[PDB]
Length: 143
Length: 132
Ligand SMILES: CCCCCCCC/C=C/CCCCCCCC(=O)OC[C@H](O)CO
Ligand SMILES: CCCCCCCC/C=C\CCCCCCCC(=O)OC[C@H](O)CO
Ligand SMILES: CCCCCCCC/C=C\CCCCCCCC(=O)OC[C@H](O)CO
Image (tube, rainbow over all chains, first blue to last red; front, side, top):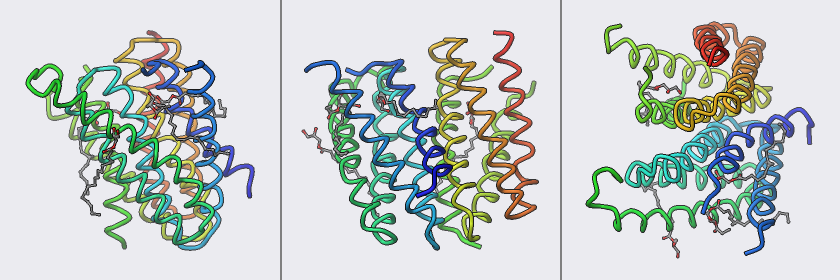
């Protein structure tokens, strides 16, 4: 554990948490932020553990990547409602979430375990968006 | 010294580059993407160098943070046009860019030099957002 690292990783999660606060997507109303606080805590904890180990550069490169495409996804799907663009982003995102998880696993089992529920959300995100997709596949404004 | 690392960091820049492709700001028209193409390679080269050194965790935590608030800033300023919210974002973004830069500097001089033109953009970004 290191407080600088952890606080740094959680602070970074404020970027996608903001997206969600602003473009509230779309069940009692505490479930969504409670689900997200847990996810942000779990992944900041995992990155913090991994950030201290030798050989972690690649996993941390993956972590930056999933984090940025996470932040991108919400405003492209729910903001611009550009469903095709948003499909590519979410699959690229899903790929880095999985990549992070697996690279975490190969350095630290706990770090990988702590990312499983986040891969589950990313799988939800992809599913939702695959549909929105080819309901709107023929409207090039949605694309 | 590593294509995986580099290609992974450059791929990550695709997220904020996408924002820019979508919410077109605002001068010969190749200038905008040429500057951003330059900015993305420079910062991926720098991240690549640092990711290989030991003690790099804190700088790489910084790198992730600026990247996300970079990605966040454009859709909040140009997308949602919420000028106040976007001010907090861009100041938070500016701060992590400077931090990435300085922590890179402490591990590898070249990595730090390679972030200066990006700190310069980040200051422009902050400057723009203050008059709005
Ligand atoms: C390493 C070589 C691979 C590189 C090339 C492959 C690119 C990776 C993309 C994968 C997308 C996987 C799909 C993500 C999960 C699907 C979600 C889904 O189908 O279920 C949700 C549905 O709404 C439930 O009701
Ligand atoms: C200011 C620095 C403080 C350091 C602490 C960092 C604060 C951000 C992290 C999590 C807490 C907020 C979680 C509340 C729920 C956010 C909602 C959300 O994330 O929405 C999902 C989004 O759409 C999917 O990209
Ligand atoms: C190996 C996989 C890599 C695949 C390749 C992905 C590389 C994407 C990054 C460079 C493209 C250059 C884009 C230049 C024009 C971008 C315009 C833009 O970035 O706008 C600025 C944005 O608004 C401010 O955040």
